[PDB]
Length: 49
Length: 49
Length: 49
Image (cartoon, rainbow over all chains, first blue to last red; front, side):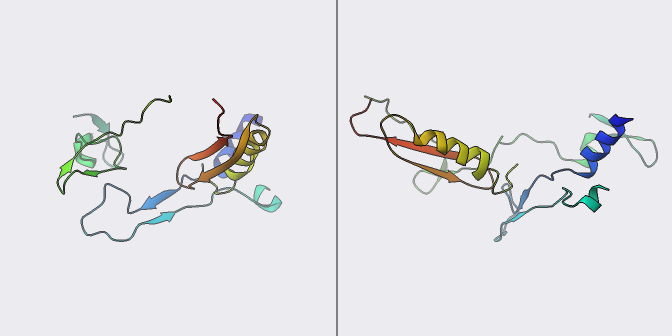
């Protein structure tokens, strides 16, 4: 059904929540904090196909 | 004591088994040092006019 | 979601475009951190209430 197509599009093409390695609360002695992100959104016609 | 239904053997596992439950701060963004010792504080800004 | 640009466009750019026409506006500025929130400060002419 069209609901299945919409659900598949929603799942496969999703936006992942960014994060920060070293965020507070943090382990003792940590000295480096770095943002981290992931890409989950499709960008081309072939990918959607 | 919250019970979770395990997915490997079907056993019941307490929430403490997979996590540590404590009472902490809602956010850890800020900290204060009054005279070189820990404390808390709030900044009060005057009303206009 | 941050994206680092959609905050600038359709949120900050669109807001600032409307701000530009504000009555008795001396200038305006905006600050955005890709991690969290966004701020747009409108500074008005001296003597305005």
